[PDB]
Image (cartoon, rainbow, N blue to C red; front, side, top):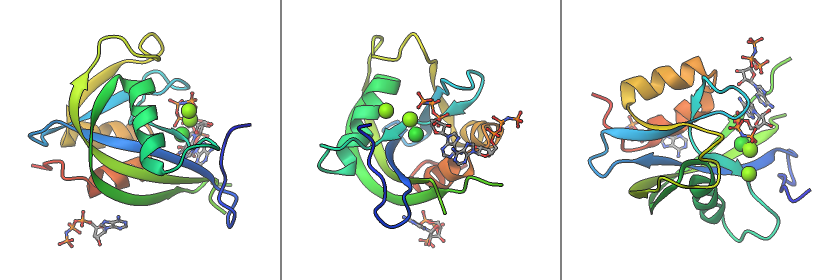
Length: 144
Ligand SMILES: Nc1ncnc2c1ncn2[C@@H]1O[C@H](COP(=O)(O)OP(=O)(O)NP(=O)(O)O)[C@@H](O)[C@H]1O
Ligand SMILES: Nc1ncnc2c1ncn2[C@@H]1O[C@H](COP(=O)(O)OP(=O)(O)NP(=O)(O)O)[C@@H](O)[C@H]1O
Ligand SMILES: Nc1ncnc2c1ncn2[C@@H]1O[C@H](COP(=O)(O)OP(=O)(O)NP(=O)(O)O)[C@@H](O)[C@H]1O
Ligand SMILES: [Cl-]
Ligand SMILES: [Mg+2]
Ligand SMILES: [Mg+2]
């Protein structure tokens, strides 16, 4: 396909965004396409031509969440551990939300909502995605 893999581990290379309000009190979440009651964050597979992970992250944040903003931090990598090597290596960025658009590519396939840190953390546990929670915890979100 168009997907890129680690030459070392064969992990699927993915990038996405922890999208925060300017006041850093809320994070943007979306429902999963697979599990429609589970709330996650925007991310997706790096494609063959893309020159950096920021490109992939901002493309997926537009496609999946209708969100435009400014990358303000590199949150490093997290690895997903497919239980009984990693098959996913995620590259996360912190984005400062500049606009949320009513219409975007996946707007009929997903719901979208801003959550406080407490609500977001319970969502990601509920979704069984501790690696996305790892990325959220590295962001400048207010954890009060
Ligand atoms: N914990 C996980 N770690 C890594 N990959 C996962 C995990 N859970 C599911 N996946 C796979 O990652 C891909 C996307 O799953 P998910 O993160 O739920 O996003 P999505 O909103 O469903 N997008 P998509 O299904 O690709 O259109 C699928 O191939 C899943 O099987
Ligand atoms: N492709 C994947 N790579 C890595 N981790 C994954 C992948 N698919 C699922 N996981 C994770 O592995 C765990 C088990 O996932 P899964 O078997 O899909 O459970 P489920 O969708 O919650 N179904 P169930 O618990 O039986 O009702 C979860 O923590 C997932 O996030
Ligand atoms: N990009 C990253 N990749 C991996 N681990 C990280 C990363 N950023 C931070 N950490 C670690 O994760 C934990 C939380 O990180 P951070 O967001 O810097 O806040 P903190 O640890 O509470 N504060 P401080 O120890 O003063 O830097 C710490 O153990 C960090 O060393
Ligand atoms: Cl993904
Ligand atoms: Mg994609
Ligand atoms: Mg995907």
